[PDB]
Length: 233
Length: 236
Ligand SMILES: Nc1ccn([C@@H]2O[C@H](COP(=O)(O)OP(=O)(O)OC[C@@H](O)[C@@H](O)[C@@H](O)CO)[C@@H](O)[C@H]2O)c(=O)n1
Image (cartoon, rainbow over all chains, first blue to last red; front, side, top):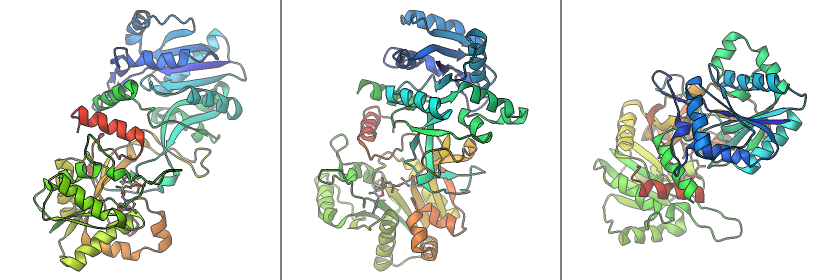
């Protein structure tokens, strides 16, 4: 079975790491979250489309689904976790308690504020997860990537041809993801913020699926202004 | 003395069509290169502002400057090189053969196809080059960065808080740039995608100056749609 996990944990402020509900901001007279969900409802192969969000946003999420006539029976809103990977695991646990996890199940996890992913991206994610167990959506780096350990000076400049900008979806065989996450120590769980890095850190391969330049994360006022252009055109 | 080097030397190859150089494409009825140049003209302290273009585009560039009533005597259009760092060094050599290089000279090198840099970015680049000798214009990485050695599977996912997207300008003390570049082999030069790595590879510091989310590089039709939005929105 194939599941979608829509991660609506918000976008943390720079000071304080306060979750801001950017997925509710308006994009051409409809919340960003609704645009993203519409893309997933178009995929008939999903058994459930699970939105995980902080307890304090669950009612507004349900109210917004109702206002924008999103009635698809596969949509469910559940409470998120203490960080992004813990929220993913809340989704996995919800699947297990509801249907039970099958050996061939896959989960397609995706940012609520990435409304411009495509049918191809979703299908390629599903197929790569079924065959290989773990997948990241990426695009080739356009800028030269540089590192710094002090926010003052360059530490290194890697070869750009080996660098990729990570997007989402990130998709996994569910049992593989669960087994890998179970291998991490409490310290690792506190430090890891990315879902594909769970797999990498536990020495299993992660496949690349190529995204799109326009599959942006709408997290700043600048990105919201750009998003209006992408949508209208 | 302070010099600007506007890098307009690439050629936009297209499959099955006449090459259309991205730096000359119209953006709100004005070529991208002119948008970029206007920012540099507003900096009084440049001694010269040198635009490098492919040989066959030099006359067209000079004429287009005249078309937009741009007569600034500091502007010179010269021939670029076969790769980006060769274009930068063509500009350095032109300065050397024209004025000679002073020990305190700095050069602000910048993509012609990045029209949305700001007064602040240029001024911080100049000051950074004067104080530290080498500087990169960067922003915090917008995405998690992923690496791959086989172009099929992830090799590593570095700690995201140490990752930055390189933009331009990149600015240098001229003698430092020249001396560092002279140390590199042809293979080392082949691997470079920017100028600041010349400095990093020769074990001299490169300082960071913050760019902007809208200091985008215009190279594909998608980027031009974004550029048009930026202009109409007053974002930059
Ligand atoms: N023979 C050449 C080739 C290119 N050029 C100029 O170079 C500009 C960017 O060129 P291009 O769009 O192809 O981008 P690159 O792949 O070179 O990488 C750049 C990336 O490193 C940098 O922006 C940033 O990230 C660093 O921090 C364009 O104006 C070209 O005309 C030149 O004058 N002569």
